[PDB]
Image (spheres, coloured by chain):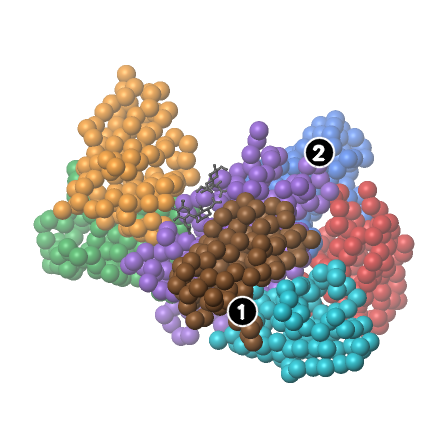
Amino acid sequence: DIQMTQTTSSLSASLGDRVTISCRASQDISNYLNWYQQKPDGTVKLLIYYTSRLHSGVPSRFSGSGSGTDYSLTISNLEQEDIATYFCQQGTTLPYTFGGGTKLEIK
Amino acid sequence: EVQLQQSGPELVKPGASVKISCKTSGYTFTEYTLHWVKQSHGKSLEWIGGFDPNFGGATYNLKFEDKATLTVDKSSNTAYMELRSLTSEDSAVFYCARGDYGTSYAYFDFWGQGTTLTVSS
Amino acid sequence: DIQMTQSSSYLSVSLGGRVTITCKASDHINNWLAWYQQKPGNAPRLLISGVTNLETGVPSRFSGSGSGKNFTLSIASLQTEDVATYYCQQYWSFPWTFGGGTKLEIR
Amino acid sequence: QVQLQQSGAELARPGASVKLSCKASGYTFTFYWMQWLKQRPGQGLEWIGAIYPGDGDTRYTQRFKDKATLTADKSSSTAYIQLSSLASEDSAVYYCAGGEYDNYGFDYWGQGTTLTVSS
Amino acid sequence: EIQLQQSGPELVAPGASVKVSCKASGYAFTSYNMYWVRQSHGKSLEWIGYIVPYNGGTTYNQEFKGKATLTVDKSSNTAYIHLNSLTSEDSAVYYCAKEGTYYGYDGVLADWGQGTLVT
Amino acid sequence: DIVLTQSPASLAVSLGQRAAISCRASQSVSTSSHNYVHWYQQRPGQPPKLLIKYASNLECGVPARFSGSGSGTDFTLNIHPVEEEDSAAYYCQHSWEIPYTFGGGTKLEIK
Amino acid sequence: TNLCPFGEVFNATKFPSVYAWERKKISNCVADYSVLYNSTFFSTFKCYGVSATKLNDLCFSNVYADSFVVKGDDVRQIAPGQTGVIADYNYKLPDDFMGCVLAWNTRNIDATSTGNYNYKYRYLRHGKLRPFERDISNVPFSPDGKPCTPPALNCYWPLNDYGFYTTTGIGYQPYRVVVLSFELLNAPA
Ligand SMILES: *[C@@H]1O[C@H](CO)[C@@H](O[C@@H]2O[C@H](CO)[C@@H](O)[C@H](O)[C@H]2NC(C)=O)[C@H](O)[C@H]1NC(C)=O
Ligand SMILES: *[C@@H]1O[C@H](CO)[C@@H](O[C@@H]2O[C@H](CO)[C@@H](O)[C@H](O)[C@H]2NC(C)=O)[C@H](O)[C@H]1NC(C)=O
């Protein structure tokens, strides 16, 4: 099984700044990464499905990038609504696996 | 005139198959299609399944996909509707209706007299 | 790199005769062949897509034949325009190798 | 719109089995897969197994090979995971999720039901 | 009508690099491929490769791996071939071709340009 | 599939007024060009017969008193002159998807 | 010993229309891949990602075989990319694809002398659709979002009919399509 390591498990940031969440893979997942948001109600929604910025019905302040085996998504300017936990998912090879997630909270 | 007819009616006891026929006359047989319906003694009609004599295959309703099969002899211009595993609910009329040219049928314009099955003991 | 060669580079049949061009195959091609024709000074035109499907917009004298490895092409009788070379091409492997060509000059 | 209505909360007792649910409405069910995810409290999601409800084909992981058995009914447009031989560890949140093209992420996600094993 | 046209005739000293265009006009350029064949004087026809217009992905015959870099410009429907490390024995005409509008196979070319020429 | 409901169940009409059989569909049936519903009457003890093709066009061999209406989900059959012979069962039929189901069926009784 | 059901999906008697394409998953058999090599029966046969020599490699996790009927002018849209009235409203292939697209001309069956109006294609819809997502809902479009009931003010029905005849050209003749999609993804067979 491929394991993915979100090394940071938590983060603190202000509002209106530019935050960045890293996510690494054990082997080269060949650009099949996708980022997930889990709002604290329990509902989970997708943000980007390919690695480089392929969006699915979401405001464009999220713009992920990164290639190879080291990836990250970022928010350009923050807002108070999207303070949630963010998962990076592997989709190269069954069995799929997920990340540990970084919890967000105001500064 | 467009002449459609089936064979005589028959009663068969449950557990045995039956081969209904439908002879036609009055048109080139390979152009138009043939379809079949069923209506159970005061209920509504429903579509069993049609045959394309030009293409060769056959299509079915999904509700009738197992108990009925279609088979056509092209020279005698007769379609052989055939059922199997007959029970009390398969005791109804059986029409041999003519549709339009293959994979364009929308209305069954000309029909036949229709045969009735009654399972018994 | 599969190969397709023709037997004769020259073939001279007088006007009103009956010609036979043949192209052998190095390895096996299933049914996939094409023929071309260029009078000098122009670009070649597609002639027989597949072995015997004539391209729409051509005289109906031509009709390819043969299957397996051996393949051929016959013209009914020549005219003033059918004095050009003819290439035999497969499209079954990746490098879609043409032939050596065969010129029909009038005797 | 497409929603995945999922069951409410449940309670259970150890050694027993629970038949969960995941109702799919708004898109065609017979054509695409359906994945099942389990989240421990405070940890990342893990992939239990996926089921193709067209003919009941199923693909499990290596850990959950004998605990979960997946099945689905076509006309009800629902999928059924039945967890078996429950110990005290399976108190978690169970998400059902599925999507059209599985390389481009799981688009549709359920609300997420929870499960406990006490007395 | 489907009109492809390349540039004018070209000439170069050996050891240099040439670029020759092939402007497509008369259809939707993002649909068909763009092929590139090579033909020496009175000789056979030899491939270079092809190029998908919207994606830019290329594939070369391994004879020409370090000699030609294919590219395309989707804005004004112009396809290029950038010849590199060119020498003599290359003196040949270079046709740009596409597949038939109703055939759909890969290698079958049915619409050709005028033809450039190099030394 | 697609189920067709009919209303009223047993409509009774007299010679001086018109009859309105309303065949409502489950989902929408129409496209921009045509309307995919055909009609059928069936005198008792006899096979059915075509009346309306594609919800507006009448067949050749009609008494010109049968003409349909409606587009979308709602469809109806109009009989403005009524006489003795058209006392029979009347059937709706849709052609939208490969399985074709027929309607429920209404009768016409005259005092 | 167990030949895969290519003999059902390719030689069927009624392909569904392109707004409501079907799919038949095929697995746990042996695939022949040799009866579809006729080059004068089919037309397109263009494959991306893999070459056309798939008899050797066993890309055999599952093979999804979608199938529909399109007009002759827009069988070119069954391909990755390719913005158009078919491919961004009815059947959108993803950008990467290990799939195989096959098509063939069926003037003999699907087209008549009076006119075929049985095949449909959805031409007008709120925005694009993602890879492989289908829509079967027929609700009347209105350009404001709020619903209408046509023939009211400038809001039509979201489908049309191909209108197949036997007298028209090649570009308006029906082309039956079948689209494979190999999905290897590190599975057992
Ligand atoms: C569809 O039908 C054709 C026949 O029209 C099938 O092709 C035949 O395949 C069998 C078995 O290999 C051969 O013996 C016949 O000679 C073939 N006939 C022709 C004319 O090719 C085809 O296999 C069927 N199924 C598919 C997948 O298209
Ligand atoms: C490949 O397909 C073509 C077209 O279906 C076949 O050619 C037909 O063969 C039948 C039977 O001999 C003839 O009745 C038709 O007139 C032919 N049509 C054409 C266009 O020539 C061909 O035989 C098939 N070849 C293989 C390999 O099965």
Residue G63 x %, y %: 61, 44
Q: Colour of chain F?
A: green
Query: Is any atom of residue C35 visible in this view?
Result: yes
Q: Please report the residue visible at 48 percent of the width from the left and 75 percent of the height from the top.
A: E1
Chain letter, blue? D
Chain letter, cyan? E
Q: Colour of chain C?
A: brown
| Crowding at mark 1 (Cα within 10 Å: few <14, some 14-19, many 20+) | some
Residue G182 x %, y %: 64, 47
Against E34, is G115 above or below?
above
Q: Colour of chain G?
A: purple
Q: Colour of chain B?
A: orange
The residue lying toward the viewer, choosing from G35 and G67, is G35
Q: As drawn, which residue projects farthest toward the top? A: B121
Choose mark 1 or mark 2, whichever is in front. Answer: 1
The residue where tag 1 is placed is: C38
Residue E67 x %, y %: 77, 68
The residue where tag 2 is placed is: D68
Q: Please report the residue visible at 79 percent of the width from the left and 49 percent of the height from the top.
A: A98
The residue lying toward the viewer, choosing from E89 and D68, is E89
Query: Is any atom of residue G19 visible in this view?
Result: no
Chain letter, red? A
> Left or right: G81 with respect to D95?
left
Mark-to-mark CA distance, 1 and 2: 68 Å
